[PDB]
Image (cartoon, rainbow, N blue to C red; front, side, top):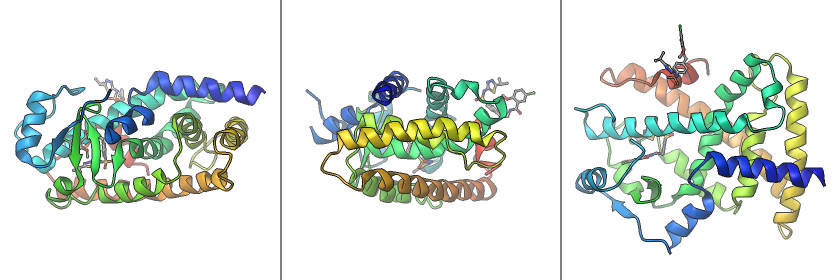
Length: 263
Ligand SMILES: COc1ccc(Cl)cc1C(=O)NCCc1ccc(S(=O)(=O)Nc2nnc(C(C)C)s2)cc1
Ligand SMILES: COc1ccc(Cl)cc1C(=O)NCCc1ccc(S(=O)(=O)Nc2nnc(C(C)C)s2)cc1
């Protein structure tokens, strides 16, 4: 009863904080939705940059690989900010000690970003420019190493994740559970974190029961994906650290350096 209303509240805050929903993404990738402009090479990328409207700008005078790397960074930073406002809409999150709130966001944001990233990806590429662009996976592998390497595993994770067929209402709860994880390092009051988590997790288990009646082992399967995202994020961080040391003409945004750093 209260769980059902809890889940609805989390879902609304998710809808309030993130513009691209899985529902919208899927109705675009599948086809009242015009087909997105396909970015498959440098020319189409340049045209997409000139023609489409994006949320922002980037450093000028950069080779393509690096330029695309900064676009992604800029998008990551914006989602970190959306996730920060969303976690503030999670009942009690704002009750935690300041250090804990920070610690949860620091260690959980990329996990949430990668779970949500799947909504806009298929095996062939992903939506960009808020759904008006579609960048092909082949075009991305055609970029310079090590930049062509960052994304492949996100694609691998996404295609497996998408087979679970979650919808926005499931994802909103999944994302709160990821942020309210009691296993982060340096947590001060973990019992207080796990108390808020258990509520979200109870709301989720029940929610999936209602929303996926003919899917028996979905709940635990979801908790396992959380394990997958954590490994995905550890790898991603190492990739960034190496690019940082290996690519002198590139730099990590301040807020992102502060995240990849400690982890
Ligand atoms: C691959 O993403 C893009 C590729 C080309 C163009 Cl024109 C735009 C985007 C974009 O807007 N991405 C925003 C969403 C996004 C953000 C981060 C990531 S990532 O976590 O994989 N980090 C990456 N950093 N650089 C990357 C490039 C060099 C592939 S991937 C993937 C996707
Ligand atoms: C902004 O954070 C700081 C603010 C004052 C001082 Cl004395 C130090 C830091 C710092 O070392 N933060 C490192 C971690 C961090 C860096 C940047 C960002 S942000 O860019 O997302 N927010 C900012 N807003 N304004 C900023 C500049 C103009 C100070 S940074 C978040 C987190």
